Amino acid sequence: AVIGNESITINSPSTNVESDTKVNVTLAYTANATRDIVAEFWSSTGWLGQAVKTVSAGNRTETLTINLNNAPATGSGYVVKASIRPVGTNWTSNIATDQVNGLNVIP
């Protein structure tokens, strides 16, 4: 019932992020088992937050809400990273990844 590779794609945000304590990341993926999908939000100076969702096998688009302590300062240099990996594992088991650099946070 399984053929081909698992995958993950960041569909949004592509360019801009609204300033808020919640950052939504829309991910499309191919999971050939139950898997974890992870979205992270980084500034130019390092990791700010991430969200994880355990997803059932299939081909789908889902949106994860990343919770931050404070709204990020306006400017560029922000990064969204995504990965799909076996449930409960850390980054060393990543099956596929995506990333978007050069994001701007708007006032």
Image (cartoon, helix red, strand yellow):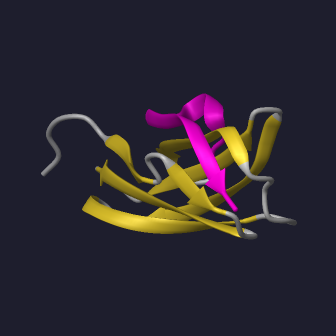
Residue 81: x and y in percent read 57, 41
> What residue do we see at 46% from left, 35% from top?
97
> What residue do we see at 51% from left, 55% from top?
36
Q: Residue furthest right?
A: 69
Report the side of 58 relative to 53 (left or right): left
> What residue do we see at 62% from left, 39% from top?
79
State whether residue 47 is above or below residue 66.
Answer: above
The region drawn magenta spans: 89-107
Image quarter of residue 71: bottom right
Residue 18: x and y in percent read 61, 64
Report the side of 30 relative to 87 (left or right): left
For the C terminus, the quadrant is bottom right
Report the side of 59 relative to 87 (left or right): left
Residue nearest the viewer, comparing 97 with 71? 71
Residue 82: x and y in percent read 52, 44
As for residue 97 lying within the magenta part, the answer is yes
Whether residue 56 is visible here, answered yes or no, is: no
State whether residue 77 is above or below residue 37.
Answer: above
Q: Residue furthest front?
A: 107
Residue 44: x and y in percent read 76, 33
Image quarter of residue 46: top right
As for residue 9 lying within the magenta part, the answer is no
Whether residue 91 is visible here, answered yes or no, is: yes
> What residue do we see at 25% from left, 35% from top?
5
Residue nearest the viewer, comparing 42 with 31? 42
Give the total of numbered labels: 0
